Amino acid sequence: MERLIPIVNKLQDLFAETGLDSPIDLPQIMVVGAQSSGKSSVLENVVGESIFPRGVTRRPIVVQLYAYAEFLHKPGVRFYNFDDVRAEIERETDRVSPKAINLRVYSPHVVNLTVVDLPGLTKDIERLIRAMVLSYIERPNAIILAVHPATMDLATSDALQIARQADPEGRRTLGVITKLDLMDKGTDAMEMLTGKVIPLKLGYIGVICRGPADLRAGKSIQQAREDEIRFFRSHPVYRRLLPQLGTNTLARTLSTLLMKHIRDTLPSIRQKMSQQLAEWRKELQTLGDLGGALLNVINRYSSEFAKSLEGLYGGARINYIFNDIYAKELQSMNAFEGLTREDIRTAIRNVPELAFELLVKKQITHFVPPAYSCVDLVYDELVRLALNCETELLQRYENLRSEILACAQNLLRELKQPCLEMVQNLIAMETSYISVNHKDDIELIQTLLASYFDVVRVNMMDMVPKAIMSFLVLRARDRMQSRLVADLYKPERMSELLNESSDVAERRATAKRMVDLLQRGMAVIN
């Protein structure tokens, strides 16, 4: 169905008019990249005209496709000059931030598509960008587009790592590899592109885009895509990969994924908008006890948190990170990894069992980093559960909402240190005792090394989830019920602090600036 992408666009403009003060969780694609990826060139390559500013964007840019353009902050403007479109992006950046710029570009050499560009990361202002990106990718219905150059490592990529912070398995995360003309054998990007190594479950698309020197001489985007097709066609190893690659393929893939994602998420979105509309109308009625309000509102958030973490979620994903990721990482760490035949002979020169203990002890140490990673991947899921609940939550939440999120996030920081220490201790117990009474020189030792290491691998795959459940996931639930209440009812700042949440009983009309937009948005879904 074509209609779905124009319906989502009408919902985005409305929210922005709203100013995108969240509330809704619309289904959309969010671009995450470092500044040196060339994400601006990827966006120019999709549109076909040179509309992105070059040579510090401080706002999200929402880009919708249907040459001319029009801007939501200039209603009914038929910009027939693409230089004025680029200059307006500079002006509406300099004029001010989470408030989106919405730019509708209409060209017929583009597909029906909608994409949101975010400020790029660099290798406190950067942390404000990094926090700003999280406000858009924590979102349950948001697809993450992770734009990485083949010039660099993709495993240690900032954009991949921040995507992991909201999606530890890359479930709703899609990879884009730029600069395939600068790819050699010495990078992860080739193995990821050929599907043999999967970090991201929506796949990998590779592109070639206008570089610095290229874009510094007026090279056309149409010509650059013709260059891109030509380069994949004549390259010795990319000739087999051409029907899965390029800007033309990327545009088809993005449109195809977005259209399906909108259709399957649309039933729940329609229910959610109706629920928020009913309750925000009650808030507008109310504005025309204080202690009972804090107790009821905080206690519901505690039950919303507990249930989601038991098994949108939460519990099923927490089970997925343990059993469908941490298990796969540990099951693909090899016995005899790094250790050569020469290492075993070196240990023998320094009773076979004494050589075995020294070799096993080194081999066991390699389970500390995935075991560490498993704790953080769960933390990344747990912090996001607050944001999932924040979108289900009644928009009617003054300084109380932000303080609840701040308390919940800081509470997760408390248990990170004991959980990590216990995970380090579990690996260290095995390296301290190496028990052979558990239920061809180098040949024998290599056999013994594998036999004990596989038993240790079984012990540390099951035990580390159990430690994370004890010191983080279970401990967080029980605690949230009373610690979240205690501080919110102890500063003495309350109820002045609570009262502070009052806004003078005036902000209620504005909540309407919020009620009206759902009434309009419901009419766009009917």
Image (tube, rainbow, N blue to C red):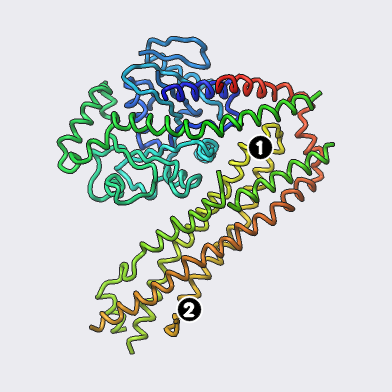
**Front residue of 347 and 95:** 347
Decide if residue 145 is in sight here. yes
Q: Which residue is mark 2?
A: 432
**Residue at point 30%, 42% (across, down):** 150
Quarter of the picture holding the C terminus = top right
Spot occupied by residue 507 in the image (x, y as percentages of width and height): 73, 25
The disc, 1 or 2, on the residue closer to the chain's N-terminal end is 1
**Residue at point 38%, 10% (across, down):** 80
**Residue at point 56%, 49% (across, down):** 314
Residue 413 horizontal side relative to residue 286, left or right: left
Quadrant in which residue 122 is drawn: top left
Query: In the rendering, which numbered label is found on residue 49?
Result: none
Quarter of the picture holding the N terminus = top left
Q: Is residue 305 above or below residue 357?
A: above
Rounded to the nearest angstrom, the CA distance separating label 1 from label 2 is 49 Å
How many residues crowd mark 1 within 10 Å: few (<14), some (14–19), many (20+)? some
**Residue at point 28%, 25% (across, down):** 216
Counting the numbered discs, the total is: 2
Instruction: Give, as a three-letter code, the residue at label 1.
Output: Leu
Spot occupied by residue 404 in the image (x, y as percentages of width and height): 68, 43
Q: Circles 1 and 2: CB distance less than 8 Å?
A: no
Residue 352 horizontal side relative to residue 28, left or right: left
**Front residue of 298 and 44:** 298
Residue 513 horizontal side relative to residue 8, left or right: right
Mark 1 vs mark 2, foreground winner is: 1
How many residues crowd mark 2 within 10 Å: few (<14), some (14–19), many (20+)? few
Q: Which residue is mark 1?
A: 393
Instruction: Give, as a three-letter code, the residue at label 2.
Output: Ser
Quadrant in which residue 159 is drawn: top left
Element assignment for label 1: loop
Decide if residue 124 is in sight here. no
Element assignment for label 2: helix
